[PDB]
Amino acid sequence: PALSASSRALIDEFMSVKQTHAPIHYGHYIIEEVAPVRRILKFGNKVVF
Amino acid sequence: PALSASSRALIDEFMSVKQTHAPIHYGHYIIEEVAPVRRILKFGNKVVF
Image (tube, rainbow over all chains, first blue to last red; front, side):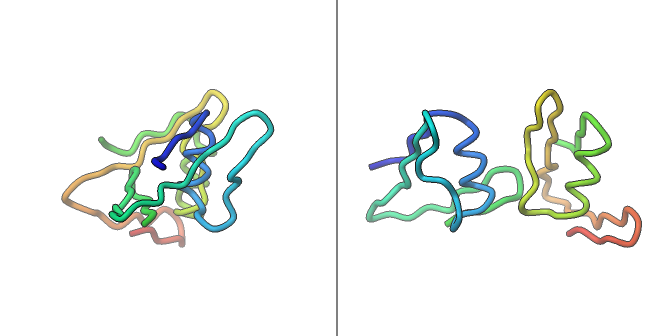
């Protein structure tokens, strides 16, 4: 599975804090990418690997 | 992109805490500058690389 965010709020909160992010919200969901490759995800300055 | 803040409260948050800040408020937004030069940000006491 790849990164799929139903609203931009989830991709923002996931990129903000990796550990305590909400995988599931009320009406919106988000799937963490799990893959044989792992990529550096940068937005602005913030970094999640 | 250069540093752009819609309201002073966002740039105060961003200087206060780098990581956990919001990029997007209700009607206000903030852009982190991405440049090959990284200046040192000395607003007040607080220092941001």
